Amino acid sequence: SPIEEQATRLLKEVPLIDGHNDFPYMIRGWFRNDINGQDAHLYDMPIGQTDLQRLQKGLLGGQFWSAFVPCPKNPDKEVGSLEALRQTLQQLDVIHRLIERHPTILQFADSAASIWSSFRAGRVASLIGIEGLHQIADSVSALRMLHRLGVRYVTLTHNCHNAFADAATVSPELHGGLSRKGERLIRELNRMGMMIDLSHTSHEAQTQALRLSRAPVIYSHSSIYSLRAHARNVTDENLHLLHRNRGVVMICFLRELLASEADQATLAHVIDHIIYAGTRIGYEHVGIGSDFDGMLRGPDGLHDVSCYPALVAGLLERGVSEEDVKRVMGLNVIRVLEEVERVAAELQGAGEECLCDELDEVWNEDIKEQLTRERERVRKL
Amino acid sequence: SPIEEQATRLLKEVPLIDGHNDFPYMIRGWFRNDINGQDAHLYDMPIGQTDLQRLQKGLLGGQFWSAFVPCPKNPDKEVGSLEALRQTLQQLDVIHRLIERHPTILQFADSAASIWSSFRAGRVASLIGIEGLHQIADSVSALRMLHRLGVRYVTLTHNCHNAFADAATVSPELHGGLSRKGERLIRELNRMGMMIDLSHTSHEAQTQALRLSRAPVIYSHSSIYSLRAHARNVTDENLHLLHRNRGVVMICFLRELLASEADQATLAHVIDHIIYAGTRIGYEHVGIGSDFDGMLRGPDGLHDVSCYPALVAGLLERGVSEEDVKRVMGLNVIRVLEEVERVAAELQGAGEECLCDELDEVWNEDIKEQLTRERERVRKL
Ligand SMILES: [Cl-]
Ligand SMILES: [Cl-]
Ligand SMILES: [Cl-]
Ligand SMILES: [Cl-]
Ligand SMILES: [Cl-]
Ligand SMILES: [Cl-]
Ligand SMILES: [Zn+2]
Ligand SMILES: [Zn+2]
Ligand SMILES: [Zn+2]
Ligand SMILES: [Zn+2]
């Protein structure tokens, strides 16, 4: 078909970059992060919506792989919070090992330049994002180390409130948006060059973050509230504030977020949501955020990662221009990561002070006096 | 003086690379890792044996900065172990922030090539090592992420036994050397390209590690047992096994490890220890491992980081040849890091399997059946 040729051409011209995929958590569920001698299965998985053969088949240009761990359930909150930090390092480890063992398919990327160079070489640009600030164990130091490990976005919450922000699906509210810590963390995320992700956060937390952020943010996997009312979807108010922010809403394939009856959801609904946002806040502020492997079943026509050419063909079929389709595929999310990087270099170049943790005093006054007396003895030599 | 000119010339020809310095822990003790607007103090410290002015003054070519945290003291061992992991990320964070805020003095290095390029540019090559396997919280995944954060050696223990090995200063013995886990970790450390450090470990743990390791190891800060009997010093047996291993013993400035009476220790004692090892196992297997800021007071003549030219002059004065002095300064520890890297590329190139953690089952059989049924539905489309 001519439109199917056109869609294939576009997929090889520019990278389709998906905002969120939980294939690393499926590896923890199925293999327990032990992928030694499991290549046959990693190429042809017995479960889930993602494997390395179907990933090639769908012609996906890039992917933000989720390093998600669940919200802590231990009655002791100290242990649960610290356990989530260790599990985060396990999920970051298996993502890096997945990329390293399959260098012909996957290539690690942490910037706009590294995405393109990966795409030139014919590989899926493999980026990383964590899903919730519960994963850092209230450590801004840990968060900066996660950035060094290759994490390029942070979802502020998952399905639990944390010290920084409110989740959408939990009531009652704790902070009623962002906390005082949350507001201060937004500055630090902008300074370090970490992309803010507003999926899973409450409507009020989105509004506050969209006004405060000095860099553009994303919704890694969220849909439109006006088409389908849900706590996880983006309101018209926040869509307009996203436009002012210069951010991107990456549209989700979750059936509950697309239709009132989940079994009615389809590829056509995903296209309706993309066109709604593209019409009202422009096609330079819309993306694709599947949430594959964060669900059991997908919409009719978007059942797995091999189905991306049908989405590209569907957008072209409805009258979205080539240039606008390319924007929705990946050019927009590349721009946001590029602008997040530019703002960070701007603020770091100006000598902005970093957010430090509240650390305990480890020395008493007796130890400090011994140290000062010792220093003055050395000065007299 | 002619020997003082000779020592200065050598310090500018090749980098003096010190094996261990705890200046990052002094920053946690004094500043609580908040170095914003503390440049005047970081250049001229009111405490300790290390600051950025004296670091320049001593003409030090490189440094393995310690990312040490104390052995956990919480009655609950789960919390203490997990707390040590968070504190490790705080210490790695402040080390990276220290290097980043002073790029004229310090430059990050994680290899032999990066050490030289830093030294060509006139900067102190800033490498990182953790002091104890209690710091990883029994996570090999975490350990691989610490390698990604820039850690290039791991001391197997500090002053506490862990699941992998026995410390020297604690009795009774737990494992009587390395555990079964410890033996398996040695293979993983060789595979990933992590330099093994045998300081603080028991004599039997050293012997076992020296026989098992496929790459050369180091003693980041240890002295000679025959000259001064102490649990922390290296025996003649282990010195010979270090020779077969192709490793390096980096001589310590700790007064307790150099003399029976601590106040009698001197620069001359450090030179006696270097010459003893250099005479018996060759000068290509000896280094300098100060342990500055891991003590209150140093030996007479080695009171702080400005005193390295006196050590170089002292070695030349005793009749150690220029080429042998250059080896002790840094060429030896560069070689070990180069060989550790070569062995890792060798083993990784041959497709050796990595050590995985013991992870809990997160899905029951009901969830796995839903996933397999869902996959087969997709196959039929
Ligand atoms: Cl380009
Ligand atoms: Cl609007
Ligand atoms: Cl699921
Ligand atoms: Cl060279
Ligand atoms: Cl011997
Ligand atoms: Cl001390
Ligand atoms: Zn997810
Ligand atoms: Zn989600
Ligand atoms: Zn130390
Ligand atoms: Zn020590």
Image (cartoon, coloured by chain):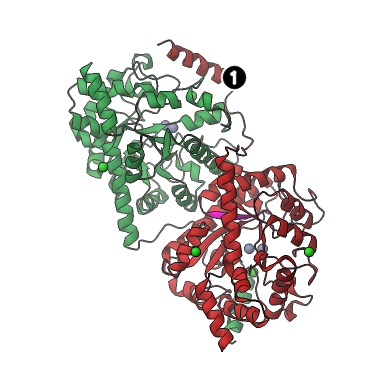
Chain colours: A green, B red
Q: Amino acid at mark 1?
A: Glu
Residue A41 falls inside the magenta stretch: no
Q: In the image, residue A61 lies at what x, y percent?
A: 34, 33
Residue B154 falls inside the magenta stretch: yes
- Residue under the image location 27 percent in, 18 percent down: A268
Location of the C terminus of chain A (image quadrant) = bottom right
Q: Quadrant of residue A254?
A: top left
Question: Which residue carries the number 1 mark?
Answer: B365
Q: Residue furthest bottom?
A: B1
Q: Nearer the viewer, residue A71 or B351?
A: B351
- Residue under the image location 71 percent in, 45 percent down: B183
Location of the N terminus of chain A (image quadrant) = top left
Above-or-below relation of B48 to B173: below
- Residue under the image location 19 percent in, 29 percent down: A322
Q: Report ligand 10 position as a quadrant.
A: bottom right
Q: Which residues are magenta?
A: B151-162
Q: In the image, residue A144 lies at what x, y percent?
A: 45, 51
* CB of mark 1 near ligand 3 (< 8 Å): no
Q: In the image, residue B137 lies at what x, y percent?
A: 63, 46
